[PDB]
Image 1 (cartoon, helix red, strand yellow):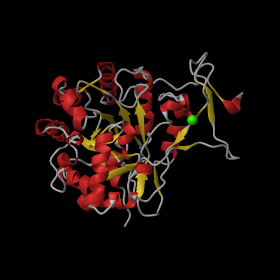
Image 2 (cartoon, protein in one colour; image 1 turned 135 degrees about the vertical axis):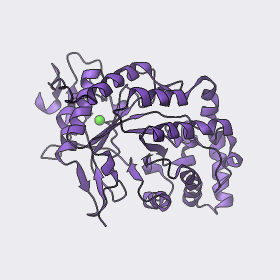
Image 3 (cartoon, helix red, strand yellow; image 1 turned 60 degrees about the vertical axis):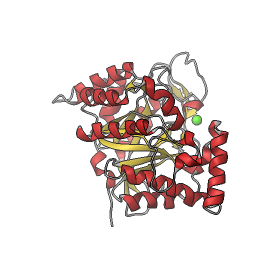
Image 4 (cartoon, protein in one colour; image 1 turned 180 degrees about the horizontal axis):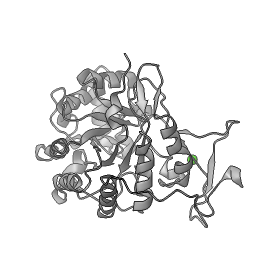
Length: 367
Ligand SMILES: [Ca+2]
């Protein structure tokens, strides 16, 4: 029938606390305290109602935050795909901290799975995986990966509320089949899929392009303006990815305030198939990086508060792609989120600074 699985998310905002996967987690765990990091987020950011954390390592579908798998011994494919037993408890501990605090949990999962190991330089893992699905699944990589992912999905069952599926153009097999696996475990999961970005066009089909962000922008590269669309029958919320950072689009682009966010709140729910409805959701990097804590901090309180208010007032949702520094939210971001949360829990909520086009910011079409 008709489904609004993300109805709980409408009018809410979230933060991100990624956990490392596989051998990367074994390398970072000795200097990290993700559990303390999660307690600090709970204490300091009560206004955020959910968190995105990690099934796979960021941009590395072959590296998992859990080890044990009742469906396949992943450690026997290649040990570097999975962390130690001691370290697999980090993700579970973080999730339980958020559950006790009443925060919903969405897990980032890079859809490519082990198929992308060589893309990140992990050639030994790639060879082991390729040998595994060839010999054990008679060359059916799609079934091999669904089986493997299912064994972790089952462990997270009832502990998490949704999934954010990255890199779905590179999923072995079909998205429909992978989402069906997820829903076979828990059909109420709130699921986003990142296929490709869509962009604002004019009445004759040309893309809109930002020409400048301000007076003497350091990066003059023209960039397109992301539009969040409901493009398939599987999704419960739009993935929310900004215009790619590599194209020189700042994650706090003024154009997101003139186009992207207004469009999110103009029509906060849309349907592709006529039965399942999906919620408009944006995922904004707070730095000039999705996951890199050392990148330039791009938002300040006043702009970040206006992003949260404009989205949530409209009945849409947004997540900050905050970063982790030894398991804690990077401290400059934490400082901002404290202030945002404190404003968002006041009644009345304090007014946000009104949006004005930055001096010397223009579209190519406006010149
Ligand atoms: Ca572009």
